[PDB]
Image (spheres, rainbow, N blue to C red):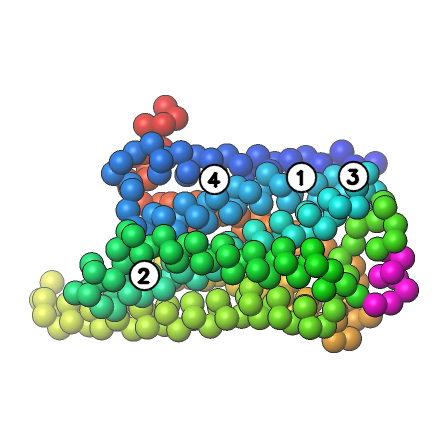
Amino acid sequence: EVWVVGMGIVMSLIVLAIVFGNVLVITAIAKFERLQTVTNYFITSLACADLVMGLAVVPFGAAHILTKTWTFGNFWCEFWTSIDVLCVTASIETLCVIAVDRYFAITSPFKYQSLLTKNKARVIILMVWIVSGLTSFLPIQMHWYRATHQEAINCYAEETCCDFFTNQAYAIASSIVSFYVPLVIMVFVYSRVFQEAKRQLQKIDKSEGRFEHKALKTLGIIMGTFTLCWLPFFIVNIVHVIQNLIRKEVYILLNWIGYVNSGFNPLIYCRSPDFRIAFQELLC
Ligand SMILES: CN[C@@H]1CCc2c(ccc(O)c2O)[C@H]1O
């Protein structure tokens, strides 16, 4: 039987990867004064969200999957669900804020210096987490998301069962707040940035005539590891409520595909040469 020892190894490796990467990024930004920049506060917020997710959400879900029972109390089921939703929405919204910051950096270069002051770059982060917590903790803990049918009531009345059942309203509102609004903004921002880059290369070629792969590669790496990781989940999240069409195993698998996005963020964003120097100093 390889379906007990085997899936544990993969889950443990995911936990180790997430924890190691996020801890390294956080300590590199904290220890070195050169890396302290307005752009790097969004990165440290994202790293904090990913580290919390890797420490809390993944291990208990892994234990639940491997054991098929919930030994802990009934309070901890709702606490764990609330933490899961909070971390996911905070991470995605920080990803949106980073793209908006880059839009403001390239599109308007003269007014960028005054706009993103270090003092005003903290209110944005404090608002992101508050908005994340107003949709994660408050609706779940007040018991406003609860479903109404025999399976849901039986699940809620048992102390060893912890499965996600939700209404139509909460599912739709949660998906809209967490995914689609932060997606349209990123699409618009990155399209405009690509346009500006193309114009710049056109000017260079027209000027130094005698003597778009990079932009496409960078935008593909940024926007193909996010849509592919999170888009499949937020469609079944609506479908399984509108209509038996979606089975539970597919839902759980598509949920767990979106968790590994936390382990890839340091590769995508913490790739500058200064980060490489800082990582070299810390480890070796
Ligand atoms: C238990 N897993 C949850 C279920 C629903 C949900 C998640 C993440 C973000 C949301 O906006 C959600 O509505 C998932 O992490």
Q: How would you classify the magenta stretch by its main secondary structure?
A: helix
| Mark number, residue 102 | 2
Residue flagged by tag 3: what amino acid is it?
Answer: Phe
Q: Residue furthest bottom?
A: 242
- Residue under label 3: 72
User: Relative to 40, does residue 209 appear above or below in the rendering?
Assistant: below
- Residue under label 1: 59
Q: Are marks 4 and 1 in contact (CB under 8 Å)?
A: no
Look at the image and give the residue range highlighted in magenta.
148-155
- Say few, some or many: other residues with alpha carbon within 10 Å of mark 2 (under 14 / 14 to 19 / 20 or more): some
Q: Is residue 158 left or right of residue 234?
A: right
Instruction: For marks 4 and 1, give the CA distance.
Output: 16 Å
Q: Residue furthest top?
A: 284
Please tell me in which quadrant of the rendered image residue 202 appears.
bottom left
Q: Is residue 214 left or right of residue 133?
A: left
Q: Which residue: 19% across, 65% down?
A: 111
- Residue under label 4: 22
User: Relative to 135, does residue 9 appear above or below in the rendering?
Assistant: above
Q: Which residue: 78% across, 75% down?
A: 243
User: Looking at mark 1, is its residue's CB closer than 8 Å to ligand 1?
Assistant: no
Asked whether 263 or 168 is in front, the reply is 168
Instruction: For marks 2 and 4, give the CA distance.
Output: 22 Å
Q: Give the quadrant of the N terminus.
A: top right
Q: Position of residue 69 (x, y in %)?
A: 83, 42
Q: Earlier in the sequence, mark 1 or mark 3?
A: 1
